[PDB]
Amino acid sequence: NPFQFYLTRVSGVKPKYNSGALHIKDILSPLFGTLVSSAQFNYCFDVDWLVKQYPPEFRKKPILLVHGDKREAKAHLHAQAKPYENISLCQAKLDIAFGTHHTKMMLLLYEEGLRVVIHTSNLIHADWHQKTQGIWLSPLYPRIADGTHKSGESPTHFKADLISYLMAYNAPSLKEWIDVIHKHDLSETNVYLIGSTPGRFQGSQKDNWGHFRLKKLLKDHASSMPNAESWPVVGQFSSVGSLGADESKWLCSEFKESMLTLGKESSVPLYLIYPSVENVRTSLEGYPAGGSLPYSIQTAEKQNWLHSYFHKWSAETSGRSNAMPHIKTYMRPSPDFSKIAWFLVTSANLSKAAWGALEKNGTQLMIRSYELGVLFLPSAFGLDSFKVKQKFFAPMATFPVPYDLPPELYGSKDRPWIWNIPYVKAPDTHGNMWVP
Ligand SMILES: O=C(O)c1ccc(F)cc1C(=O)O
C-alpha cells in the first residue's frame, strides 16, 4: 500500500473485515516506535480511556491534549487530566463565534523518528468500537543529523504546510512540536495537507485554508480530462450545518465550484452520502449511533432542498454497511465510478464553519473552526488517475474506497438522520426507540 489509508477496527464483523484495520492500541504499540512524547489533537476526550490505550511501558510519557473547550467544559477536561501528572493541555483559540476544534491528529515522537497520524475518531471508546472511521499513517520520519542542513521537505510541501497549520494556533506547547518537526525528514510524504483554521483570509492567504486550499491544489496538481463535466463529485460526512435557503447560497456556488476544479484552464452531478434513519436504526449500535450524527431539526427544516442530494450509507466493499460513518471523505469519480481523480479524508463535515464561506464581496474567506485532512492526488504517485479497489480488503495502484459505488439515492420513504427528534415507530437492533 502506497496510500497508508486505513479503517478502524469494528467489533462484530468477521475477521476478514478487520484484517488490515487498525485499533488505537495498534497505532500506539511499541511495534510502531519507542514513544518519547505525544500530542493528541481532538474534539472529545475520555482521558482515563485514552491513557489505557497506550502501552503500559509508555503510559507515563508526556502527552499534550489539544482541544477547544471553554468555561465549564474546559474545567471538566482539566479535571479529567489532573490525576495524570504527565498530561498537559493546550486550549486552541476560537475567537470567531460558533467554531470548534475539530481536527483529529496524533504527533508521535519516538526514539527512532517521528510519525504523524491524521484521522477521524474522537478519543472515546464508542468512536473506535462500531463506527466506520478513517486513518492516514505517515511514514516513520527519521531525524535530520545535528549539523546537517537539509530541508526535509516533500514534493507535496507537507512539512512546511504542517508547520504552517501549527503556527496558526500561536501556542507555546505547539511551538515545541514545530521545533520537533523542523528536526525531522518528511520528504517521503506523498499526500497534501488540507487544513482549516479560524480567521478571515484575504489576498494571498485566501488559498491557505478550507475549500480555497482544495481548489488551489486541484488547479496546480490535477489535470482536466475530456468530458470532465460528467465526472461526479462525492461528499460523505457525519454532520450537516446550515447551508442557506437554496443551493445557490453556498453548496453549489462556492463549495461545489471548488470541488469540481481540475487544472489551470455546472452540470457536474453532486452525490452527498449521509445515513438515513433506517441506516441508523439497523446499525450495529442502533439509534445511539445517531448521537454521533449531529444534524438538528432546527437546521434541517430550513433546508429541505438539500435532502434531494442525499444517498444512503452502504459499505459492502468493507463489510461496514452497519457500522455508521464518522469518517468524512470527498472524491471525484469517473462517470462509471471505475476511477477517481482524487480522494480526501478529513475531519471536515458538510459545514460552512469547516470549509469557509466567502465574505466582503467575495474577497475574504471566513472559517470558524480547526479541521485537517489529507489529499491523495494521482500526480503525487506518478499516475493520471486511481483505479477504484473493488473490495476494500482484497496492482497496489488501486485506491481503497471504503464504501460502495455508485451511491444509492434515498428512497421516497427514507429521511436523513436528525438527532434531536424522536423515532418510536420501529425498534433498533438492541430493542429500543430513540427519545432525546
Ligand atoms: O465528532 C466530532 O468531532 C464532532 C463535533 C461536533 C459536531 F457538531 C460534529 C462532529 C462530527 O464530526 O460528527
Image: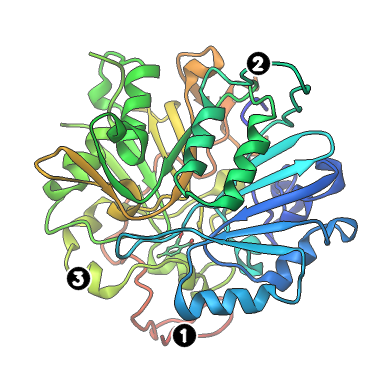
Left/right placement of residue 141 relative to residue 95 reads right
Of the two numbered discs 2 and 3 in the rendering, the one whose residue sits closer to the viewer: 2
- Residue 234 picture quarter: top left
Real-space Cα distance between discs 3 and 1?
22 Å
Whether label 2 lies within 8 Å of ligand 1 gets the answer no
Which residue has dot 2 on it?
150
Amino acid type indicated by mark 3: Glu
Real-space Cα distance between discs 2 and 1?
60 Å
Task: Find residue 347 and report its horizontal and vertical position in percent.
Answer: 47, 50
Which residue has dot 3 on it?
301
**Mark 1: secondary structure:** loop
Q: Residue at x 44, y 54 (%)?
A: 313
Which residue has dot 1 on it?
433
**Mark 2: secondary structure:** loop
**Mark 3: secondary structure:** loop
Q: How is the image coloured?
A: rainbow
Identify the image quadrant of the N terminus.
top right
